[PDB]
Amino acid sequence: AKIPIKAIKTVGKAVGKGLRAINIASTANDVFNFLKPKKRKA
């Protein structure tokens, strides 16, 4: 049916936001620990 380009783009958008969601979630991890100097106390 008339829905090719929008078909591949639609799926590409899913995997695109899905893979990224895992990325922004992956970067948030290392980062979440990146701002943790040796301080420890307070």
Image: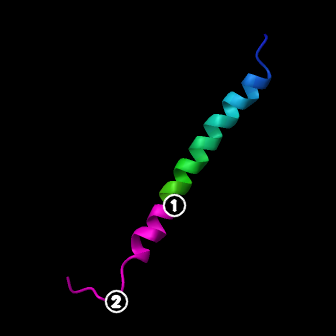
The image's colour scheme reads rainbow
| Residue indicated by mark 1 | 26
The residue carrying pointer 2 sits among few (fewer than 14), some (14 to 19) or many (20 or more) residues within 10 Å by Cα, namely few
Left/right of residue 3 with respect to residue 39 in the rendered view: right
| Residue indicated by mark 2 | 38
Q: SS of the residue at dot 2?
A: loop
The magenta stretch spans residue 2: no
The residue carrying pointer 1 sits among few (fewer than 14), some (14 to 19) or many (20 or more) residues within 10 Å by Cα, namely few
Q: Nearer the viewer, mark 2 or mark 1?
A: 2
27 versus 16 height, above or below: below
Tell me residue 22's x, y (percent).
53, 52
Left/right of residue 25 with respect to residue 12 in the rendered view: left
The magenta stretch spans residue 38: yes
Q: Residue furthest top?
A: 1
In what quadrant of the picture does the N terminus appear? top right
What amino acid does circle 2 point to?
A: Lys
Tell me residue 35's x, y (percent).
39, 76
In what quadrant of the picture does the C terminus appear? bottom left
15 versus 26 height, above or below: above
Q: SS of the residue at dot 1?
A: helix
Residue at left 75%, top 29%? 8
6 versus 29 height, above or below: above
Residue at left 57%, top 43%? 18
Tell me residue 13's x, y (percent).
65, 35
Left/right of residue 24 with respect to residue 1 in the rendered view: left
- The image quadrant of residue 6 is top right
Left/right of residue 19 with respect to residue 34 in the rendered view: right
| Magenta-colored span | 26-42
What amino acid does circle 1 point to?
A: Ser
Q: Residue furthest bottom?
A: 38
Q: Earlier in the sequence, mark 2 or mark 1?
A: 1
